[PDB]
Amino acid sequence: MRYRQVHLDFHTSEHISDIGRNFSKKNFQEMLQLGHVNSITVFAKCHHGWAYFPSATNEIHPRLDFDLLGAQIEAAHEIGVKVPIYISVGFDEKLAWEKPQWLMRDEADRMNWVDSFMKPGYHQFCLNTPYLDLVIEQVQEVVRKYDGDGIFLDIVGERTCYCTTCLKQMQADGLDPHNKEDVIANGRRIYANYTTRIREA
Amino acid sequence: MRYRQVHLDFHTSEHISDIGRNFSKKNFQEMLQLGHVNSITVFAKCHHGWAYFPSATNEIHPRLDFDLLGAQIEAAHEIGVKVPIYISVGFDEKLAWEKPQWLMRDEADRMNWVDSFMKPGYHQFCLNTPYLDLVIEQVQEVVRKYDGDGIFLDIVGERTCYCTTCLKQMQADGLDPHNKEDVIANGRRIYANYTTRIREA
Ligand SMILES: [Zn+2]
Ligand SMILES: [Zn+2]
Figure 1 (cartoon, rainbow over the protein chains, first blue to last red):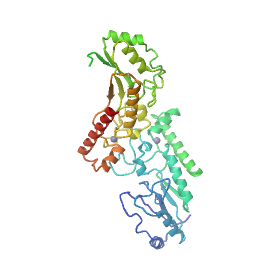
Figure 2 (cartoon, helix red, strand yellow; figure 1 turned 180 degrees about the horizontal axis):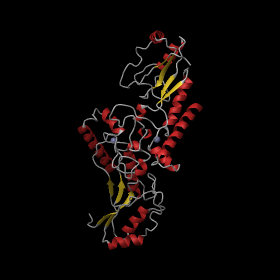
Figure 3 (cartoon, chains in turn purple, yellow; figure 1 turned 30 degrees about the vertical axis):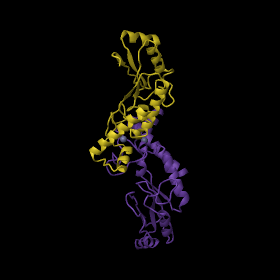
Figure 4 (cartoon, rainbow over the protein chains, first blue to last red; figure 1 turned 180 degrees about the vertical axis):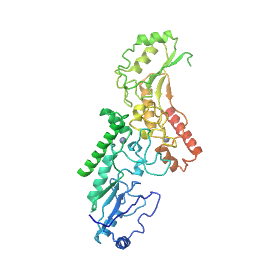
């Protein structure tokens, strides 16, 4: 495990243009060397939900014209820098707008982290929904196609969720959604099911 | 237009059994005569979302074994009583559980009439969504298959809606969701579009 890592965030709005236009192998390598960096986690998929590579299971950032993920792995590997790859799991904001039925709900029907679409911020998906199948596909694509040094999966953990899918499933399994213990235990199974499916894929 | 009408409600939970088991042509006719009733609006589709006939575009109440709508029209028509037919539009609670993405939202993401699924009551659909296409199909089926004397369409009117579909559509049409006037005017178009499609179908 390398001692000198950078976690390179790239949560980038669809409403910003010319993504990566000022990227260069030379600039990326010079700054890693200036920083004495020997590992840099770079983005395949951000909170806004875009891919930074020409993806078949997800949509590339609509203002990105080239394989930024590919260019970063190559530039770093050519100077002996490892490159783990980041995938946002809990957040996919451009999918949130198409599939709000897959978002987490509390007892009072509230989304997190932000409780409406009329305010800025991100809306967390429930991994007890078919969103899990889309995550596995997208993780599989990145692991097949890119020579990364690992996967960092973000916005995950044991939750308590009262979404339509969870409430139906709890009732069918004889659990009581009004019993907090039952919902906490459901969420322990939901999270373990997600990490088991990731390790097997 | 007949002077002596009854509006016969039939909002019936999936969790009640033996629907219609004590129905009879004789009982239905005796009570219409006791009441001096010359028209009775009967249900094709209730707030809970079930059909009271063996429907191909909607699901029959899961505890109903026979064509209750058909039996009521026949029993009434055979004693000269007209039978308009009721269809819940705004409410379809069993669909609400499958398609929460089609439900109305206020500025703060709240459903109406009831602001969560963890409380009893009904959740109103937005007619700016593909739910409108399902309503037209279901209205078409009832009008084709049954010799009714009219259609009563319930839980409809001009709304203000901030659901994901409405917010995207308003932004694409250059309307401002933060401008109340813009959202009111959008809802006037949404409602007129619904009543125009019903009259044409
Ligand atoms: Zn859930
Ligand atoms: Zn709407």
